[PDB]
Image (spheres, coloured by chain):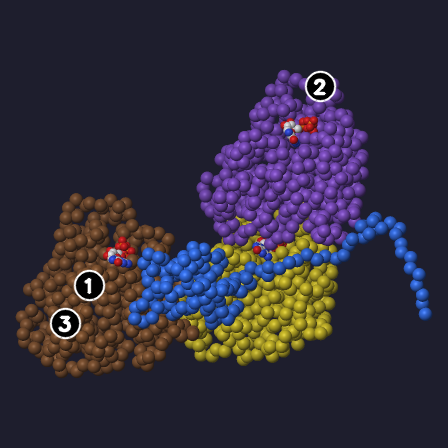
Chain colours: A yellow, B brown, C blue, D purple
Amino acid sequence: MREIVHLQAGQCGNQIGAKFWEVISDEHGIDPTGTYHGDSDLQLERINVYYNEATGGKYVPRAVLVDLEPGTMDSVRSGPFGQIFRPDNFVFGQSGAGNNWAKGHYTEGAELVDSVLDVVRKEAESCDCLQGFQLTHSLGGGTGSGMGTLLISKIREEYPDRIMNTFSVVPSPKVSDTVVEPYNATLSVHQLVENTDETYCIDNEALYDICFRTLKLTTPTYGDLNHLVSATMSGVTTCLRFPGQLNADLRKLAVNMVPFPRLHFFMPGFAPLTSRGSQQYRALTVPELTQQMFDAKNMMAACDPRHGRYLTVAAVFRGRMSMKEVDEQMLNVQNKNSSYFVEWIPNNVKTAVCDIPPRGLKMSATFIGNSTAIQELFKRISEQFTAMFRRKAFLHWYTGEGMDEMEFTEAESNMNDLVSEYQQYQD
Amino acid sequence: MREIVHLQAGQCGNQIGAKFWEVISDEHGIDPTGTYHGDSDLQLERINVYYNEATGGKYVPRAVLVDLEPGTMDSVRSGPFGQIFRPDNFVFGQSGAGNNWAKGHYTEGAELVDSVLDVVRKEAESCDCLQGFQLTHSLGGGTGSGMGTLLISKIREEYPDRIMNTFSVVPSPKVSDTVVEPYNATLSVHQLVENTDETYCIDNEALYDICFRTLKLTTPTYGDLNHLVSATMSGVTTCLRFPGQLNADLRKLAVNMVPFPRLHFFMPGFAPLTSRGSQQYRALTVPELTQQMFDAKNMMAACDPRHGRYLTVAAVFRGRMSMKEVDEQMLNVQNKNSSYFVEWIPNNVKTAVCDIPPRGLKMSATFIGNSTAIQELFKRISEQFTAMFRRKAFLHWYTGEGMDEMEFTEAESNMNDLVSEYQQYQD
Amino acid sequence: AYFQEDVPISMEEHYRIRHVNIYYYLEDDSMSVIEPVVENSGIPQGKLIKRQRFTKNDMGDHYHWKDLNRGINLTVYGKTFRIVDCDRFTQDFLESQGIELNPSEKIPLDPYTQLRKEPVRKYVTPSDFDQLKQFLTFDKQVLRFYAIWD
Amino acid sequence: MRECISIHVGQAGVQIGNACWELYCLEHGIQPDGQMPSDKTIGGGDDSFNTFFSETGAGKHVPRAVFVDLEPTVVDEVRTGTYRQLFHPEQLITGKEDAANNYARGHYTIGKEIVDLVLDRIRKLADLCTGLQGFLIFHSFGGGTGSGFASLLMERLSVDYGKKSKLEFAIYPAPQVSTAVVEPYNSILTTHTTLEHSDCAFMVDNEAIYDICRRNLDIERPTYTNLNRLIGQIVSSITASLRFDGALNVDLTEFQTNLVPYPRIHFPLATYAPVISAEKAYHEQLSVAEITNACFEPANQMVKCDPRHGKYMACCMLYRGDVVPKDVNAAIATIKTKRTIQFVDWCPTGFKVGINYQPPTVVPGGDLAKVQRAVCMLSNTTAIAEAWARLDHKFDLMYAKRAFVHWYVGEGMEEGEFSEAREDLAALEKDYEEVGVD
Ligand SMILES: Nc1nc2c(ncn2[C@@H]2O[C@H](COP(=O)(O)OP(=O)(O)OP(=O)(O)O)[C@@H](O)[C@H]2O)c(=O)[nH]1
Ligand SMILES: Nc1nc2c(ncn2[C@@H]2O[C@H](COP(=O)(O)OP(=O)(O)OP(=O)(O)O)[C@@H](O)[C@H]2O)c(=O)[nH]1
Ligand SMILES: Nc1nc2c(ncn2[C@@H]2O[C@H](COP(=O)(O)OP(=O)(O)OP(=O)(O)O)[C@@H](O)[C@H]2O)c(=O)[nH]1
């Protein structure tokens, strides 16, 4: 059978993975102690996709957590679902990273890469047939970036045949916390784009936009932020694990969604967000879910593609619906705003229709879109990197680490190539 | 199915929006909480003209409130029927207006118009098909006029196929309180006549007169004033939602009542008023009903019509009447006084007969007619404007916000044109 | 006072329960409902019912304080409420009149509100370490039992 | 795990070390006995305390600190004080003669025969230690004993163990107030001898402390007890992240990476925003917007540098207590939008954020208040070179008249190092001006 091994890196991962796993546990009905409670046939029957089998109604997560500072492991283990993970599935070094990507990329990794590869091949051969791997981290997150780059570089040649989902978060346009974030971003992208196939983009400022629009609760928590994005990844994973006459495989998505070797970056999106009183002040219909999903405010990925155009979109609806509402809705948008699409491809939409919704609500959906939106993002990173490289500020640490400026030069060349290609194909 | 979308603006027009909505809700028999109390299958059948449905028997109105002062909306929200409006449907700014015109026309509208257009397009997509829109505001109101000018300007072009009912109140001939008030009105009326189809012309002085004519109770509330205006507005809307041998469309009335593109000013007319003896001392017969209809005192819009001459007249009847009696009534009134009609068009009368009685009595009517009447009104306001512009008192705020005298000049040219035109059609 | 409500679509709950404050004036017998404001609530707080008098039954009657007591429910323009308890001058004046007060009752708390924050509970238990005290305090202290086995 | 080594050199700094350990005992409930009340948590040394105290199986939290001095007076007094059992005996190292403010006397004539013992003690700490992230040295430039001896010991540790961090706080010379006219000499000697061996240096001044004390503490007769409590609170803030748990944490590694841009230049400045009394905190209000405006308020800085004289490179803010990042980053954005503050083009981003949920702590019999949100400011900017200019334009005159150089040659030194130190400085100011050049 086909299954997946999860990878979580970086301090961002150290919380996002926890939230995502606890949400999935809530969905399939696993108590924090781990003793299954039978209430849903389908959740009972499609669980080997992630959970392996332990003794006595208990199940192990096929996830691997990595870090260097054991305090994060302490927090995760102390969390509401830390007990459900394994000690063996935890591995750490005995030093700090301090998000010097070079430190992590030639010094800090070389001594744990072997062990983590042993554990990952252990789990892989424990399973029977994989679809592939997904890794959760930050492209601005130094530990996550440094570890994940090498990890994917190795798994590419070790298993050249699987699906390589990368789920990474984006630095804030208004304030980056870490000053070296441009450097980290370059050192990440220059190899990530050539090793990966699918990359997701998520933005905290867009999350705060979401909070100021639909949450309307003044003070949120990053826990709630993780709640939303975990819901998004849960939604993209639901299609595989539920019955229903729809197409599931991430390959069946990627072949539709990937025109070129250089086209990898995607824009998630969630479906009805209830406001303070909308709970009993709204009406749940396919038309209004469609309208909400295709709305500027609902967007959370990078920045408005109102400047740009759209190449492909894949939408997964979930609940008992009918082919006709989705078909007519897509034709309606196609004819309504027929200019902001691109004439290259006709009918850029890919539909999936899952029968069983999330527990509690009736009809829901989720979105993903390949469109020209990341341009201003890496444009900003370009201007930051040029301004920094102009006077080698902060660069002496990397010199001492054994880094040379030629690396930065080819990285900026690569990102310039992506800028030019993305502008060119439609403009 | 054809619906109407309702707009509420200006601190009074908001008064009236509350009162009008609650009147309709009570007529259709709805609690303050939105749960229907089953009494009238016909009313339940035709609720869909105004009310959407939110799951769990909640009929969210297709109305939108817009203003800039938070406390006003707090009051209307905390009114006994404020909960029926939506937290979604409350767009507003964080500022006052100063009872200016150019301020709300340039300075602050530009950053609220976007949101109001987005919400109105959302609801327009939600509903099926429209006869048009209706707006409650004040021609003299600062914020209401400043909004509505731009709003109707924005809607005219992309929706040139529907009917834009306008509803406002003239300041009193004797006093306007606000002193810049004619400045504001002479600004607005230009764009209003430019974009208008149908306009209801109301002043409260005649309403105080009516109160002292037939309710005899000395001291009413502006709430009671808005009760009366709510009934008067309901008059036209009664047609669609009830069966009967009549034509219902606003076009059905408006093409008939509008001889030339330059006729948009219409005067209300109501059904037998009640005194404390009249509840059992009235003689409810169509003879005296129509006598009252064309009773000079029954008129409540501006002032005596007997100075001028009628152009068109329309009577909507509500109840279990027959058409021959009203028809011979029209016959007899033509016989008695044909003098103050015109040779331009004979048979100036139209009769529509809706057959469902109102809540409180059996048979009634609403009169709407246009005559050679508004000459003295806008003539008066014109001497006002000449006097004030004789030295341009107060102009400096408007100039500082950015305006110029030439616009006033062509506007006054427009009003003098209306003077001449109406005078001639009479002459 | 307080009142319940049912959520049809949301992920968490069957129902929500909300607390409110009732002010009855002695001037014109107006009454006002005010909700206290709590952060992250996700409801529009503030004023809920402005200044006016209220209608008990159809005719036009008016809620004269001569009929209100503890432990009473009442329907008011639809939404119905229940009275829990009152404050100092209120019961003093009301017993000065002589309204027989009813035994009080607990005001419930919103499970949604509590699960928003945390379980308010206790912690602290590590492993077991007290050897030094025994070692030093009981230097070469022994017992001597004479036992028999059959 | 995460723990450091505390070094307190100089009967200059020993009283502030005393104060800071006294503050440290409160929040953990370290009694002047050294043992806890009933609740048992002692074990394999695995909980918050272990970052500061090495409780062995004794039930006695013994600090990983060392005090070294050449006067027996204060050290004998403290071992006659209260926390004498708390302190380990011979990590209180004492001498008999002082340097008499003479840097060279403190660096050569006496420095040979005590470095051996302190080496032994530091290694017998380090062996049982496992984390050894770095050292917190506390000294003084105008050191009547501390200056030269500290320079020598940091020299030797730099040459022996070069793979961890080194942090320095120091009382700065008062720009217009003096306590010994030896100060320009000993200051310049320490500075230039340490520049190629000092990772990070943070600066404090008594006059600025005093001005704050009668501006917002509003008590016109302060004390060193006040000064030392404030600076101890500062260091408690800077180490809270390591000490406790939090949403996101930062470390000395991150500090030494982000704050300093270049080689050499490593001289930022500290600030504490909610420096206010109990009654003020009581019937006033505290929140992120006003504390953030305060952190850039120019008169609360402990160095008399005019902000609009200089320009900014780095800003690390530690927010401690109850906050969410929304209004935090909103406020820092509003500050970026503010026009008077002048960022160089070198740092389009400069905001190193650290959020620790745990609120700070009051002390019994203290003068602080029951804070909820505190923010500590560590900012590096160019406005400090004015201090160096002030120092040099007096160093030159005293060099020219060459007074007390007879003392220095008599104690057995020359003029060559004094010569070279001045162009070391001149290089520092020229580099400041070059980096200021956009
Ligand atoms: N979990 C989590 N991550 C956050 C949060 N806010 C920002 N992040 C980002 O998540 C990124 C990834 O963290 P890691 O990869 O584990 O950290 P790292 O590799 O040591 O590199 P740094 O970015 O310097 O922390 C960080 O760089 C932060 O910028 C948050 O509230 N929670
Ligand atoms: N709500 C309310 N409005 C009233 C009442 N009486 C008169 N009004 C009218 O409300 C008018 C103004 O209302 P709006 O249309 O909201 O005007 P605005 O743009 O908000 O600015 P203003 O005209 O200065 O109030 C006044 O000119 C009055 O004529 C009343 O009793 N209640
Ligand atoms: N560190 C510290 N400095 C103080 C204190 N009170 C005043 N100062 C300033 O700190 C300087 C102390 O430095 P030194 O005189 O060299 O101290 P020392 O080398 O240990 O020798 P002693 O003066 O005997 O303590 C003085 O010049 C004062 O300006 C204090 O309590 N602690």
Mark 3: which amino acid?
Met
Percent across and percent down for residue A249 are 58, 73
Residue in the image at 60% along x and 54% along y: D247
Q: Which residue is mark 3?
A: B293
Instruction: Judge from the rendering whether residue D159 lies leftward or rightward of residue B63; answer left or right.
Output: right
Q: In what element is the residue under mark 2?
A: helix
| Residue B42 position in % (x across, y down) | 30, 80
Amino acid at circle 1: Leu
The residues tagged by marks 3 and 1 sit, at their Cα atoms, a distance apart of: 23 Å
- Residue D285 seen in render: yes
Residue at 45% over, 59% down = C86
On whether disc 2 and disc 1 are found on a single subunit, the reply is no
Query: Tag 3's secondary structure?
Result: helix
Question: Viewer-proximal residue, A162 or A216?
Answer: A216
**Disc 3 and disc 1 on one polypeptide chain:** yes
- The residue at 64%/58% (across/down) is C122
Q: Which residue is mark 1?
A: B217
